């Protein structure tokens, strides 16, 4: 059940506990939660941002709700204020929706960066490792997680009705098993140097090392990319979806105009921690993969 469809149409939707249970069980099992009727409307004064020329550099436009800081775009202060307001509203609406849908996580949901992506996917071309037309779980070389989950909310805001074309791959445990013969330990001392030199924000844990290896080696495995089990799904304009992108294999093939919000969640806040990439990797390699993990005496 790679995609679980929900009826909720509002960012303030009321959920029964039965729907909450369906959502958390599906999310933690590695399904995409799909809300075809959950549109994120833009204000008239924001429609001008549906324009790829707002991107000023190599990265997409980003907003940090914790610090109220907008990056990746240049321009007049007034335009930057409006664009910050758009991404801040996305941060607020997604955060409220997640608290309505996932009370089990309580206050453990920690918001991270908002992304606005106005460039058409089908014209993109990057290095193999950065090429998100290749199935991957999310792992970012400059930003180790220390084991925390990467939970993402996505909304297709295309104003011409164009879908966002994804592919969704096989379960994480099967992906890990497929790539296990290709995994290797880090070179001794290298991660410490990456930290000392400011290449990584924080220290890259062994977990983050292996997630990066899965991400990178999986993208370079051309036979796996072509032949592994996967479903193609078009997320319609005006829809929203929610997914642990560190667990669900995903790729994007085409589309334009997306809002995305990242949240972090500690593994011990999950309903079924044993389903997390951290615990699956720790079991598969029989070792502790994050030295900063808490210790449970019993
Ligand atoms: O742009 C998209 O639709 C998805 C890209 C992706 O791989 C991600 O956001 O993690
Ligand atoms: Cl539903
Ligand atoms: Cl100005
Ligand atoms: Cl090291
Ligand atoms: Co991704």
Image: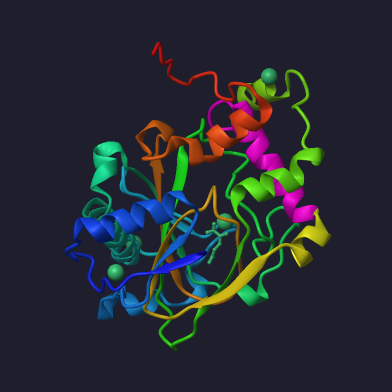
Q: Quadrant of residue 200?
A: top right
Q: Is residue 82 above or below residue 279?
A: below
x then y, percent, for residue 256: 51, 76
x then y, percent, for residue 261: 39, 56
Furthest residue in direction top, as rendered: 297
Magenta residues?
200-220
x then y, percent, for residue 81: 29, 61
Q: Is residue 93 visible?
A: no
Furthest residue in direction bottom, as rendered: 160
Q: Is residue 131 above or below residue 240?
A: above
Q: In this orientation, which residue lies closer to the viewer: 197 or 220?
A: 220
Dominant secondary structure (helix, strand or loop) of the stretch shown in magenta: helix
Q: Residue at x 60, y 74 (%)?
A: 232
Q: Quadrant of residue 43?
A: bottom left
Q: Residue at x 77, y 65 (%)?
A: 227
Q: In this orientation, which residue lies closer to the viewer: 54 or 144?
A: 144
Q: In this orientation, which residue lies closer to the viewer: 68 or 111?
A: 111
Check if residue 213 falls in the magenta segment. yes
Q: Quadrant of ligand 2?
A: bottom left
Q: Residue at x 61, y 29 (%)?
A: 283
Q: Residue at x 33, y 67 (%)?
A: 79
Q: Quadrant of residue 183?
A: top right
Is 37 left, or right, of 28 in this rendering?
left
Q: Is residue 8 visible?
A: yes
Check if residue 295 falls in the magenta segment. no
């Amino acid at each position: 059940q790679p995609i679980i469809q929900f009826d909720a149409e509002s960012w303030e939707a009321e959920f029964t506990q039965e729907i909450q249970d369906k959502a958390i069980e599906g999310l933690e099992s590695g399904s995409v939660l799909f809300f075809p009727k959950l549109n994120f409307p833009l204000l008239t004064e924001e429609l001008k941002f549906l324009d790829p020329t707002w991107v000023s550099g190599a990265k997409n436009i980003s907003y940090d709700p914790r610090s109220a800081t907008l990056k990746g775009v240049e321009g007049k202060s007034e335009d930057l204020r409006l664009l910050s307001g758009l991404l801040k509203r996305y941060a607020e609406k997604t955060a409220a929706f997640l608290h309505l849908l996932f009370p089990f996580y309580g206050s453990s949901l920690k918001i991270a960066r908002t992304s606005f992506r106005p460039v058409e996917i089908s014209g993109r071309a990057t290095s193999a490792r950065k090429d998100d037309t290749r199935l991957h779980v999310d792992a970012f070389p400059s930003s180790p997680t220390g084991g925390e989950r990467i939970l993402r909310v996505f909304s297709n805001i295309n104003p011409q009705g164009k879908p966002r074309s994804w592919r969704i791959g096989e379960p994480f445990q099967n992906y890990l098993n497929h790539l296990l013969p290709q995994l290797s330990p880090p070179a001794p001392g290298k991660r410490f140097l990456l930290y000392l030199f400011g290449i990584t924000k924080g220290y890259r844990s062994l977990y983050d090392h292996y997630m990066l290896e899965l991400h990178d080696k999986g993208k370079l495995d051309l036979e796996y990319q072509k032949n592994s089990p996967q479903v193609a799904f078009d997320f319609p304009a005006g829809s929203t979806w929610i997914v642990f992108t560190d667990q669900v294999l995903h790729a994007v093939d085409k589309g334009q105009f997306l809002l995305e919000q990242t949240f972090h969640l500690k593994v011990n806040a999950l309903k079924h921690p044993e389903k997390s990439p951290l615990k699956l990797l720790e079991t598969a390699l029989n070792k502790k993969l994050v030295s900063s993990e808490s210790f449970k005496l019993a």
